[PDB]
Structure formats: structure tokens, C-alpha cells
Amino acid sequence: GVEGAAFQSRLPHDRMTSQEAACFPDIISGPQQTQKVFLFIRNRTLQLWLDNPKIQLTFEATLQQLEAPYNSDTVLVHRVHSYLERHGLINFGIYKRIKPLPTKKTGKVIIIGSGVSGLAAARQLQSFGMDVTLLEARDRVGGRVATFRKGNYVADLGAMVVTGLGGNPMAVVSKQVNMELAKIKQKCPLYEANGQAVPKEKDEMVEQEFNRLLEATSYLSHQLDFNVLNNKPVSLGQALEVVIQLQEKHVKDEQIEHWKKIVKTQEELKELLNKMVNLKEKIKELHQQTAEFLVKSKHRDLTALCKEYDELAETQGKLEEKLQELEANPPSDVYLSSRDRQILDWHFANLEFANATPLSTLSLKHWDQDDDFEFTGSHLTVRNGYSCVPVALAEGLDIKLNTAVRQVRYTASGCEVIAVNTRSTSQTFIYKCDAVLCTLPLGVLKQQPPAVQFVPPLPEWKTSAVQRMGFGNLNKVVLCFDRVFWDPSVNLFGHVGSTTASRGELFLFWNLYKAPILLALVAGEAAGIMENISDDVIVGRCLAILKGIFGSSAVPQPKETVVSRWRADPWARGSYSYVAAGSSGNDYDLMAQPITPPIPRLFFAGEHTIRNYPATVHGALLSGLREAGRIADQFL
Ligand SMILES: Cc1cc2c(cc1C)N(CCc1ccccc1)[C@H]1C(=O)NC(=O)N=C1N2C[C@@H](O)[C@@H](O)[C@H](O)COP(=O)(O)OP(=O)(O)OC[C@H]1O[C@@H](n2cnc3c(N)ncnc32)[C@H](O)[C@@H]1O
Image (cartoon, rainbow, N blue to C red):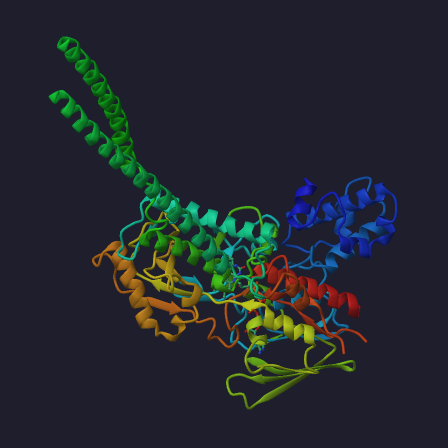
């Protein structure tokens, strides 16, 4: 009942977390029973919020809706409610307030960027009773949540998947905005470069070989410490390559031992044939040979020589039998065929899409450190378009579009930030405030000449963490036809590339909209490279692949086409962060720590600051909530 509400909030239902011990020391240092009832009140208020997240849950409605034993200790109920409301576990997202937020607002803060992190932090700080204003360089809100809308056509160019609802705050936000989510059919047929389908047996054989290779690299790192070789951190690509080399030699070694057995039996047979012709000539020359007793003795010798010959002929029979049967049963010739390698490269490209970077750059030890915080349930796509979430989050917020910040000043006296209108950067704006929450993407902070100056310049640990962490890339091309020529029962289908070097080029195709739209991904080393290619020839290559799969007859020229270039986009400089070889999971927490030239005044939020949920939009949401909570807890 209430345990489900605790789980949905990413909390253990029968034990208090560390932040609750920090905010409620009188309980962790007290009796067990009051800890248990604290947990019950927390879970019950969470359940009340989650069962009807459309309207604000007040302390008053909380008190009135709790049941008999707990409704009387009003002060602890209010403590629990205030704790939960401060940290964004209740009254977050877009909800109808019971009383409109107060007129006078104690504290003014500017927020860089209008992404999901920025919008969430803005809404939290607004309903906390503070003055908030956003500066967004782009001409729309959401940032990396980009939905191309034209006529009947809807297509997400950035955020596109909801990675499960079990514990996901995106479940609450989807319920609030009435966004319809549809399951993804996890059936992905593959098609080779010529267009012929990959048979079932080969498909699943290569798939499970890929999985075994990945588990082998996991082992190499987590029980042999194959983490630093030659004073160099090991990538996932290195471990994959060396495990492939190991299995290729297992193949070669079994080949060698088979050849050695066969040649040794061949030598045995040649020498036995020598012995046999020797005995044959002995038998012949004796066959050519009291005289009655001599005849009888000669025959007594000849029969013995003949039984000798025939016993050895029996041994020869079983030995030629053995040679033939080992001529029949050899081991594998190649570990992977050429086509086997191409299919395995498709699976590698799928992993490169999952991490938005080439595995040549992923920390073998830490690339999947977030894995233990994944949500339960099935992955869901959005049909209304993911922009329905940022735009819905933006109503009622003081958002200044087309204002790119170029300088951020933070001193103990206050904070001044210099922004500039984008459409002609001669006009200049300047904003004073008490705090600044930066939600700039890591790609913007990484830029070769700093697109935003910081005065005083950022600390050593901050800039070092910015440089160590990885910020990957992943692109989409969407094709809008008039007719649907593909199988409407499959959401995913793959195209296997010819070369390993270009295995992530148009390797996956999505039919996740029942409107006639097809989405093709570009991941890995191709992502940052095919951005240098005009849209027309990329859609030409897509049409070539689709012609090879379906025939030149059944595919018309598309009626609308869109291409993403996220690394080129000056407001993104890539897709999402990844754990680079030199980096670790602690670098996200370093990105999360605020700066103080004294009290902290420059705070950081965004997808690259949430250790347990990076690379995802629910991570940006939760990071915005956390930073708003700490800002309001300091300034109020
Ligand atoms: C590019 C791409 C991003 C995502 C995805 C795909 C792409 C192509 N996937 C889809 C595939 C997938 C599947 C499964 C797992 C992972 C991925 C999405 C998905 O299936 N799930 C998912 O969950 N997150 C997906 N993701 C990740 C992101 O979607 C997510 O990580 C959030 O988008 C992070 O958002 P946030 O941290 O807020 O950063 P933004 O970039 O959103 O906000 C910053 C704002 O700053 C403005 N700005 C810039 N420079 C400025 C300046 N100088 N002055 C003022 N403003 C400035 C920008 O204009 C922007 O608006």
C-alpha cells in the first residue's frame, strides 16, 4: 500500500535515508517506535501526493487525510511535510495550488538555460516564495528535449524514451501533463548491407556471443583489475578487442591440436604400412619355400606369419577408421566470419547509441556505474512529443528567450551575470541577483574557447572534472512519408553496416509513431562525422538502405525530412555525458558541488551532475529539484 509509494519516490520503505537523519536527528537518536511512525507518515504523505499529483498536497489536507493514530501529532506531520516539500518529493512538476503563491518574494535568482533541469528548479523555487528568472539562449524551451512538429508529423530529435515508470518522477510528470506513453516492442530484426534479413539462428547466436563478450570485460575489470595498463586507463573497446583476440586464439589452438592429432595418426599409418610390406615380402618368400616334417614345419610357420599380418591388418582397419572420423569432425575454422563480425558490429553500434560515444572512450570499470539505479518496467516512447513536458513546465515562469549568457560574476556581495540578445549580439543585458544556478550542458562548459567566462575563474577541481568527464554525441534523421511501407508490428529494425569503422551509420530504425514517420539513428564515430554532410544525401543513403530492405518499388521519396546535428549545435555541443576512461562516478558529484568565494552562490544542475541518473531527462529533473531544495534551504 504505502510501501509502493515509498518505492515510487526512490526511497527505502522501512528505513530512513541519510538526509532524513540530518534533518531529523531527534528521531535517529531516539526510540525505534517514533522512527517507525515517522516512516509511516512519510510514506502516507507520499501516497497521498502520488495518488492525486494534479493538485498541491498541503499540510492541512495531509493532516485531514491521515488516519486515526497519526493525525494528532500535528507538529511531526508538519515537519515531515516540510521536509518532503523542500526536496521536491511532493508538490513538484505542474500542479494546481490551493492558495496562489505569495505576492512578495524573498530572494532573486537567475537560472542559466531552460532545460528540464532549469524548468524544474525554477518551478520549485517559484512555489517556494522566491523571485526566479531564466536565461535561455535558444528560441524555444526544453533544450535537448526537441520535438519537430509540422502538420500531422511529430518527431523527437532529442529526448524520446521514458526508461521505465518504477521510481521515475517522469511518471508523475506524464500523469500531470496527460502525455500518452506507448510500449516499445522489443523485437528488432536485422538486415545486412545487401538487404537480406539476418536469419534467426545467426541473429541470436551473435547476440549471445556479444553478451558473453560484455560479461567477460566486466569480469576482467571487476575481478582482475584490468583497469590501468601501461599507465593508461583501459577503455571498453580495449577490453572487447582483447577478449575477441583471446577467443580467436582458442579457435586457432583447437585447430592446431586437431592438425597435430591427424598428422600423428598419419605417421603411425605410414610406418605401419612399411611394417606391412616388410611382412608381406617375408610371407611371400617363405611361401616360395623327413622332408614331410619340413613341409609341415614350413606351413606351421606360414600360418603364424599370416595371422600376424591379419592382426596388424585389423589394427590398420581401426586406424584408418580413426583417421576418417577425425577428417569428418574438425573444430571451427574462424571464430567470427566476416558477416558474423558485421552483425557483432551492429550490436556494438547499439551499445554506442546507448552511451552516445565510441566504446574506445568508455571507462571499462565505470561506464555502467548507474546500472544499479535503473527503473523497473518497460521502456515507453511518447506520441504527443516530449516537448509537451518542458513547454507545460514553462507556463507561468519568467523566461527570457534568445539571451545567451557570456559572463558570470560571483562575489560575496552578490552575483552579476552578463547576457546578450542572440538575434544580433550587439544589444546587451545585465542581471544582478543573490544566486545563480547554471544548467549549461557539459559540452558548453567544455568549449575550446570558453563561451561563458566565470569571474573569479572556476576552481581547479571544477574545471578538471569538466575536462575529465566525457560528453558524447548521437544524431537522428526523421523521414515523413505519405504511405507506410514497413511492418507496423515492429517498432525497431536494424541495418548492419559493411565496415566496423562505420557500424553506427543509420544502424537502427524506429517506427514508434503510427503516423507514417521513420526515425534512423546515427551513433558512434559516425555521429560526429556525418554532421559534415548535407541533409539531402543522408536521406539518399537512408532511402538506399530502405530500398535494399523493401525494394525500389515500394518506397516513395519522403515528403518531409529533418536531421539533427547535436555536436554542431552551439547550445548543446553533443548529446549527453558519458563516463570517460579517466573519469569516475565521483566526477558527477564534483559537478554537483556549489562554489563560494562566506556562503555559496554559484550552484550547478543538469544531466551531468546527478550521479545515479545521468544521461537522462529524469536525472535532469531530479537535479533541478535537488539544487532548488538546497538553494531554498540556504537562503530561507
Ligand atoms: C541529445 C539527446 C538527448 C537524449 C536522448 C537523445 C538525444 C539525441 N535520449 C534519447 C535516446 C536515449 C534512450 C535511452 C537512454 C538515453 C537516451 C533521451 C532519452 O530517451 N531519455 C532521456 O531521458 N534522455 C535523453 N536524452 C538526454 C537529454 O534529453 C537529457 O539529459 C536532458 O535533456 C538534459 O537536460 P538539461 O540538463 O536541462 O540540459 P538542457 O540542454 O536540456 O538544458 C540546457 C539549456 O541551456 C541552454 N543554453 C546553452 N548555452 C546557453 C547559454 N550560453 N546561455 C543560456 N542558455 C544556454 C540550452 O539552450 C538548453 O536549453
